[PDB]
Amino acid sequence: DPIRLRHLYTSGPHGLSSCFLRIRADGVVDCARGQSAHSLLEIKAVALRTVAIKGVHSVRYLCMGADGKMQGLLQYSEEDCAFEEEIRPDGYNVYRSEKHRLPVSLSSAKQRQLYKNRGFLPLSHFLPMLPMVPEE
Amino acid sequence: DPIRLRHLYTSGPHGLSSCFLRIRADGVVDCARGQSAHSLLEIKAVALRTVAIKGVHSVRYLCMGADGKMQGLLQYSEEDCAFEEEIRPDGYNVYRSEKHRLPVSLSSAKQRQLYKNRGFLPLSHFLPMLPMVPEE
Image (cartoon, rainbow over all chains, first blue to last red; front, side):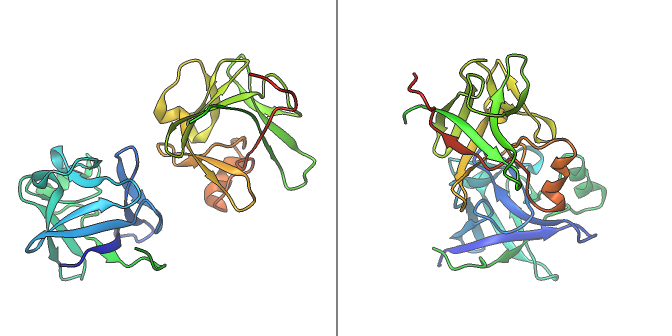
């Protein structure tokens, strides 16, 4: 199916923390305060509900490593960079990794303990936002 | 690409504050009133729009530390001393640090609060000036 250019938005319960998934040139994955060139992602279907996410600007694939820690890799590998896209009741998406048994998330090392301490991960629900300006 | 020898010029709104980024022998980074041997910088491309800045006279690399505070280090480290060079509408350049999420600036500790209080940093727009006398 068609390719999608979007900005993945998430936030904490307070709301004051607006976070757009950003893939940096140095391979780091963090939170951007608003839509930017580093947060513009290319979401491509690889299988049924499975997708690959690539930073348009950094040209790095969103990949999952140890503990579900996210990073941007220049080289794509299905097992670490392909995720099952699922819509949640809140209308946001969760991107799950089969191999790592965890959803993509911008949670910190300390926050990741909540996946088995409460059964969830902070900053793991993402709403694909269309860019505020046409682009392709 | 080729190496560039320049003097980075900036100023305050009053204009009365002419500032050339100076890298001192004692590692301190401050404002020079005019072009001098301490303000002669070597700007070298490391990647696409990424550059390294070294004081010719002090032989110190322009590096960013805590709060974006600038200092001159004898030892180069990409994460703290490499910046993305971007041209602004005023024709001046802003040198951004991916790791520190801030632009190079000669702002004081008190002035740095303006980055999130207004979204900018004083003395962060720099115009690379060619030396007024040939040199290499």
